[PDB]
Amino acid sequence: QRLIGGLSTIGAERDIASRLHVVLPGSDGAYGEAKSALDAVVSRWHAESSWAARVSLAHALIGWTRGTNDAIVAAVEEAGVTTYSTDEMAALLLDLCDAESKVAAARSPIKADLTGGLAEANLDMAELAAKA
Amino acid sequence: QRLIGGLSTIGAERDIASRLHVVLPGSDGAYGEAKSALDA
Amino acid sequence: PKTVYAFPGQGIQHKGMGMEVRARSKAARKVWDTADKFTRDTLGFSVLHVVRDNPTSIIASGVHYHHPDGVLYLTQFTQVAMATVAAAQVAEMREQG
Image (cartoon, each protein chain N blue to C red):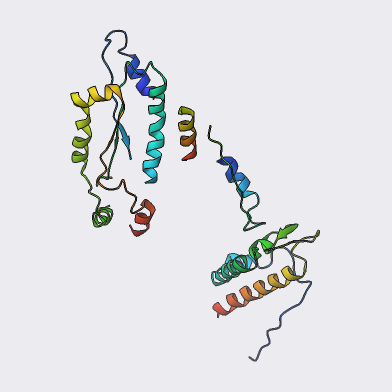
């Protein structure tokens, strides 16, 4: 949030109506830690009005990517959650940066889900970790 | 949480089955800050 | 040879009995683990703590016992300490052949 403050500050008085745009990653308990990391920036967004003319938030809950293991991928595809590669995840993440999504995120923080089935906590991380 | 760790530690091996008990306060945006303080 | 294993009585107890045996062996470490697991699951105290340190007063399942020279020195705790020390020593000297 120090970073978003500085990057919103550096082009302030030169180029008004030029709004920075942020994409937040959110990576069950790790998703809870991610949402706790979220609802401080979003709370400060709704609180302070100096951010409102410069920033445009967007958040994506990311799914499960098979790069940074094969037994983990086999276990989660037996579980049924759809995994992704890094390029697939990058395309399905960077699609939030077109003109429609930034005009929509100019009003309110978009809170998008990209998780292909791990949003339901059927299996847990240590439950897979002992198996792995 | 350092406090609850220490107070749970000091009566550990002397008195087993003796469990410390904590009451957390949570005080809209202030309630969101409180819930963020909770879910750690 | 035909031998005799004779086991002692009171007055043998002190703080830290057989802790070097627990440090040396592994079967003795196993029988210390089964002993203090059993007594913390049934009686309500840690016999490993009662031998390794000598606290002033501990709480059992229901009540608390107190002995100002040390809680190692009264009746029940002396006897269970002698029991686990004799069992650990004989398990070590039977796994050593």
